[PDB]
Length: 48
Length: 48
Length: 337
Image 1 (cartoon, each protein chain N blue to C red):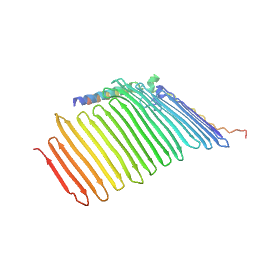
Image 2 (tube, chains in turn yellow, orange, brown):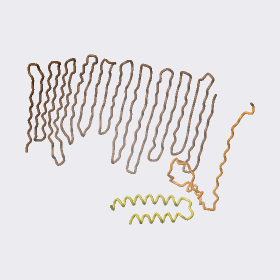
Image 3 (cartoon, rainbow over the protein chains, first blue to last red):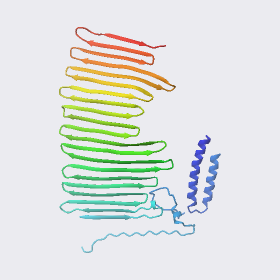
Image 4 (cartoon, chains in turn red, purple, yellow):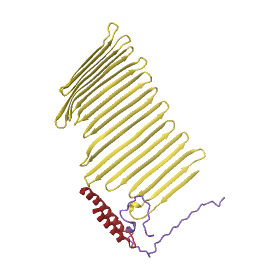
């Protein structure tokens, strides 16, 4: 279970990095930080 | 909201955002510019 | 009467892959005496993909000539794919066509040291005529790739020969394939002239280092009207590796007016290497012989099946004769306990 969850978390982290890279390189009003925080909380949720 | 990229999807995934390639720092108050110009004519010889 | 239709569509942005350069043209010509000429050329250019086409149809009454080519080429860092097709069709009195198809790719993924390549030429030459068919194609192709999970290399050569003329059918198939681990030649020959005869000949030769060799040869000659059937069926199989032994199958017979004889002979001595160093001793003798005549007949079947230490011979032989009637059953078998 630890190995499988580690692999899934690695894939999720790759996706998160890609999405954050897309978000940063786009115009936004105030929501970049909100999305980044949501993604980080999602990573913590995955670990839990 | 009106500064979002506009394109025809030959490739759906963008390695670099079109705005990022445009290097703009667009804000809400920046007036985005759009202008469509179309002419159509059907010609009949006046020499009958 | 002629129409000129030209199109130039250019949608430009950044990310050159996203930029295309389209051009389409269409031209038609038609005099009152009706020789017609049509031509088309469509071009698009985007960095990701480029495909080109040109077609020019002509119609001089009975004479019709069609030319149409399309070539597409994909270009990316990992791989560059290339496909090209040229089509030449002409119809004056017969309908003869050629359509050539070249395929190519060179895919390389150095992340795991993977490289794949395959060039395929798929060409058709065909002729149609009332009373004659001339069809043939060459399935020529080769391959190579080296990957830690998979590595192969070899050449494939397939030729298909078909033809029609009169009441006789001619068809020739011959497949010759070579590979690092598998080598095989497959020739097939068939011919039958109207309702007179039928010639069937098979040539299968499979080469495998791990299994050993296997030879299958068999030939057929059937003559109609007289009801004669005489096909020669033989085969030799050498087994190597986990299964080691020899399997021989002799299939002989002769169907003749008022005379029919069948000779089937299946023989095998097999020693199967099971896991844990256990060997199954399979040795069997399955032998058949039949004869048929209007006044007398006979059938004989003999089996001598033996497994490891258990041996079984089953004997049966029936013979029909006016002088004597034969009826015997021989059953014998031992099973060590």
